Amino acid sequence: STGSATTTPIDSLDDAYITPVQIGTPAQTLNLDFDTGSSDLWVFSSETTASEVDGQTIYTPSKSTTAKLLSGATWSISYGDGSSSSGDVYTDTVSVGGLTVTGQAVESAKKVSSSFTEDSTIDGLLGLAFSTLNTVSPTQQKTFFDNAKASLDSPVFTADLGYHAPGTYNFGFIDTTAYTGSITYTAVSTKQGFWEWTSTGYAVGSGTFKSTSIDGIADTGTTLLYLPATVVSAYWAQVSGAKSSSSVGGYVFPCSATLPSFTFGVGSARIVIPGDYIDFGPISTGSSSCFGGIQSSAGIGINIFGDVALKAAFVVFNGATTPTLGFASK
Image (cartoon, rainbow, N blue to C red; front, side, top):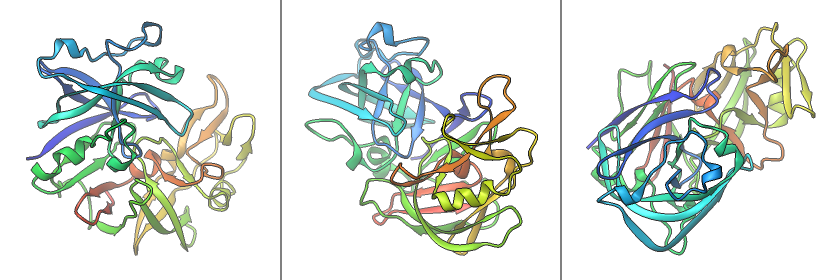
């Protein structure tokens, strides 16, 4: 089997991407944030505290003939931005782009933090990291990809995120029309439950490539590119008027400035992030100060190749017995 679904930016800045997902029988379609940095599929639901729902589409398991309570199961998750959610668990039929999993754990939110309530466009998350990070207790649950894997033509999914435009998540096949050149594959460590890999270095604009190992994760659920302070300083030093602002919480730059590209290494290959991808707009409405898309990972404890980086590539998440990551230009 295979599946193929379009993923769409939630706003004009690509702050996140939503993908439609069919849950239950008859289908209830919710727009989920596909997140290769976590491993829970959770949704706004008929069980979510009423005051914490504001515009989202909810899953109502009582209206699904295939929903079954996963008796005794609870879940609770916190994300790197300080947001959180928790609740109980059903199993149900879940389809993505024509690919169907029966018996998928669908984690129903009883509580969500304000960040989730305030974002009307995201109805929940669909985790695509390794199932060892899944928070369901007492019985850890598998991700949608883990459950689908054996049925797939090939044990892979691919992320092809758009810049200010829709893109594609494919399951079970590599679309050879969707990228240029070849796909370069690189080793993955699963020890922390992430798609964790080592970049071979970087360049800023037309500058010379610096060979240096940068360990980090491929995370579709993080918006920006978070790298070591040395790397990030070298980038913003090439932007006139850029500064790190403690009050704003990162590097900002005048919107009149030209942003250089940023290149990162994948083995001997190179992925170029165009300068425009690094512009995340005014820090507040009407401001001439713009928020940067490359920020320091200092204090996160890990480097994160988020959407800013991933959307410059066609990315293969290879879930073979020994997982690997592939990157191609596009």
